[PDB]
Image (cartoon, helix red, strand yellow):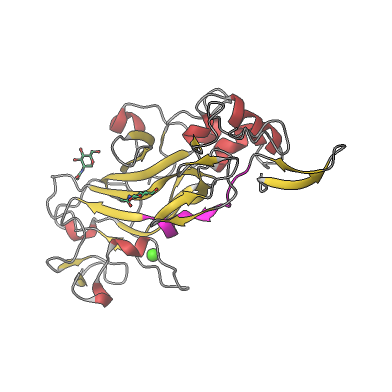
Amino acid sequence: YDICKSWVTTDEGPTWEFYACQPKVMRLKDYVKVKVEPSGITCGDPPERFCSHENPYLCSNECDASNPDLAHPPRLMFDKEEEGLATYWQSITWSRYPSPLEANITLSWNKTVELTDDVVMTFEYGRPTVMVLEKSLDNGRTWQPYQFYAEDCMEAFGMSARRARDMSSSSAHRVLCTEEYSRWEKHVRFEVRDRFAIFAGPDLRNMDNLYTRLESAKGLKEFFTLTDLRMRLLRPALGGTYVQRENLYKYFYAISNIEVIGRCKCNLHANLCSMREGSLQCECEHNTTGPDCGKCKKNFRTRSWRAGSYLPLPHGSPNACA
Ligand SMILES: *[C@@H]1O[C@H](CO)[C@@H](O)[C@H](O)[C@H]1NC(C)=O
Ligand SMILES: *[C@@H]1O[C@H](CO)[C@@H](O)[C@H](O)[C@H]1NC(C)=O
Ligand SMILES: [Ca+2]
């Protein structure tokens, strides 16, 4: 689905032929607007000591937001790292214990995007005991749970622990709770590739079946769609025991990387998506308009707008505006 139109030779002469088309897969973290809340959740204002791997007993490592060499701003979750040098955002220590240590990390695209691979969240001082990943489809006006993470899913959310890998073709779009990334390894994953594998096989060689279901199965493609993601961090790493009240300088969130892989949502009417008026927008084909090619162009409204289709394989139906 790389081609929107092609100049073909028929029994009547040369014409333009139209196909369902999709833009390229991007490094979505490159287009992210980050916001970390609440105010003052990020270490270093005022300067604060913490326990690091190098100094785990004297705990004299300092986070100071006014010193570039000692600051951990949110921008460090999205930079290009050099070998042996992981850079990370860092929260305040759990000095307010038993008050919960909570951080809301919001990722905004101001464009509907489609996940094509796993969401990978990389932690430096242990992965959370409790975290919820949420998604928005209307630019943060509304939020819905997308994935739950807990060391104990039943204790945290009252949900049975399940894997995306254990789902059937009728439940590939189900929001699950998992213990795989929290149970006492830096990566927390939101399993996209495993959900494709339900339809395409674990080798992803049955692409035909996946394109067929992305079309025929209700809410399947919308499941991979979003304008925003939010990581609600609820409880930090506990090291497999109860909180050590004598040393709270030990507990904090440290995130070196958030990898988000996918393409713009162009309703199968565009193979190009780029920055237009300061935000990602589709370069619409098929006589369509709007940022997602969701509407017909002004002088092309003889028929009601339809999205393009992956079907019939391999090029699908363009379902152009007339
Ligand atoms: C996180 O966002 C939720 C609303 O989605 C809000 O109720 C909660 O208080 C926020 N947490 C913090 C620590 O700000
Ligand atoms: C969102 O993108 C639209 C264009 O699609 C733009 O007009 C609008 O100003 C953007 N909003 C923000 C907050 O960037
Ligand atoms: Ca980093």
Where residue 290 appears, x then y in whole percent?
46, 42
Where residue 84 appears, x then y in whole percent?
44, 73
Residue 25 falls within the magenta-colored stretch: yes
The residue lying at 46 percent from left, 73 percent from top is 82
The quarter holding residue 1 reads top right
Where residue 183 appears, x then y in whole percent?
38, 43
The residue at the far right in this view is: 11
- In this view, the residue in front, 105 or 154, is 105
The residue lying at 61 percent from left, 37 percent from top is 197
Specify the quarter for ligand 3.
bottom left
The quarter holding residue 56 reads bottom left
**Placement of 131 over or under 84, stated as above or below:** above
Range drawn in magenta = 21-32
The quarter holding residue 93 reads bottom left
Residue 127 falls within the magenta-colored stretch: no
| Whether residue 55 is visible | yes
- In this view, the residue in front, 273 or 247, is 273
| Whether residue 122 is visible | no
Label total for image: 0
The residue lying at 36 percent from left, 67 percent from top is 87
- In this view, the residue in front, 173 or 185, is 173
Q: Is residue 210 left or right of residue 105?
A: right
Q: Is residue 108 left or right of residue 94?
A: right
- In this view, the residue in front, 143 or 246, is 143
**Placement of 90 over or under 314, stated as above or below:** below
Considering the image in quadrants, where does the C terminus appear? top right
